[PDB]
Length: 544
Ligand SMILES: *C/C=C(\C)CC/C=C(\C)CCC=C(C)C
Image 1 (cartoon, helix red, strand yellow):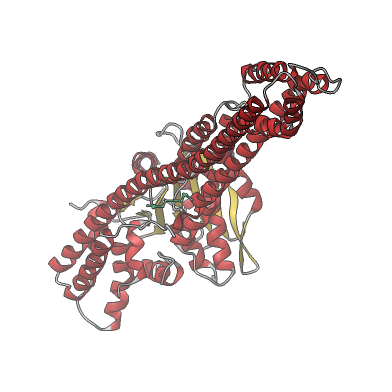
Image 2: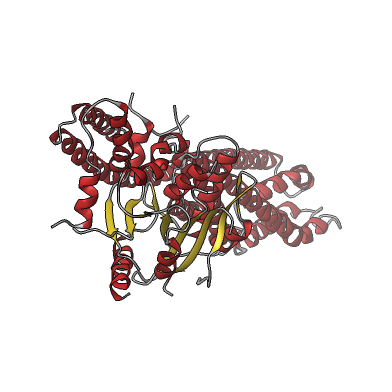
């Protein structure tokens, strides 16, 4: 994707914030990961020039300009521009939204970092009231800000002043706090503490008055943005692309419209709702496909059908596990298991009925010649019983010899062989070539054969009774095995992010202590203690 000019992403019309549904349409189509650079500043600050230079070349709100990334292959550079800041009831909301949506946050101001510049940057002192970190109900929620806030860049335009001092050390010294307790001191320290604690990284660029040395001060700012601005990522390594950014815009803007707080965790869970249900359908579609191309529905045994389900079920779970995240209480995985169980019971009852048709059909083919040779009285005769017993067994052999009958072959036949039991005993009793005590022996031999066969059917209806419950356990163990490995990867990734956060907090805490601010160091030490406790957490399995 390569838009020629910026399009309004969020409009500030009527005191309302609305996401331009056209802008979301373009976002949904972008599949590549995104580096989101937000350029923020009061109106007529010169942001439009940085916006055009990063791209490679109204009415209030946030404007978006997505061009391909110049120095990262296969990535999209998303430029966000705040239009109309300081002209005012939604100004602070636009500042907050630019923090939530960007991976690098560029604040642009004119002149130097004095009292007027800090007063104009009053939005940072309201982020505690505009942004929420955690969804769930003694440290502040804003202590989590540093773990997902963007890098901070403060560009100073028309910086007519001599630094020896680097632009970065100028920022560092400017953010040093004042000692004292009067409120001009607390007013002085509040935006500086906010910048130092909420953003993981700080950078400063100074620009002369606009020129070939204004052009390569700009060119070095762009190259720093191109080399150092990271992919927009949500907690858990989720790389934000088009549809995922659209998810964020909608969640945050709808939360503001409702009078609620845009909450980073709520946005992640709302996005997980979308992709997890899509993961379930992708999992099912893979199951149906690998199954329809692997089962021919007179299965020889039941275990042949259960093994095809088991192997198809394993891959479907693999599909879902790969495409899912934040499956709180495993609701979507349990939903996938329910649908896979429903599919398994449908393949089974269609399996047995394809067998109860292949065999019931071949009874009318094999045994109806004999059935109507009995009709014409062909066996009603001296010696007719032995001729009948012999031909019935030849037919029974021809029945067992047919290729693939299924799991119903014995039940269908033994039901028919007893359908004609009295018809056979009539042939036996009227045969005049047989002893009447040899008639005795044969009535015993037949009812022993019937009782033996009628017991092995009940023995098989038990073996299949228990193959089903047995496979129900491997299914469960397969879900358990794959979820366990998924939950460990997520924990290892969450721990990697928390160690990074722990290092940034420890660095800022003792820096505060070194500068002599025991109160602020004490607060940060509690944030560290709260974070180290959280790092020891392990998510549980919802079994019942
Ligand atoms: C550690 C996780 C456990 C013990 C739960 C794993 C089970 C599911 C997820 C549910 C899927 C399995 C069935 C519905 C039988």
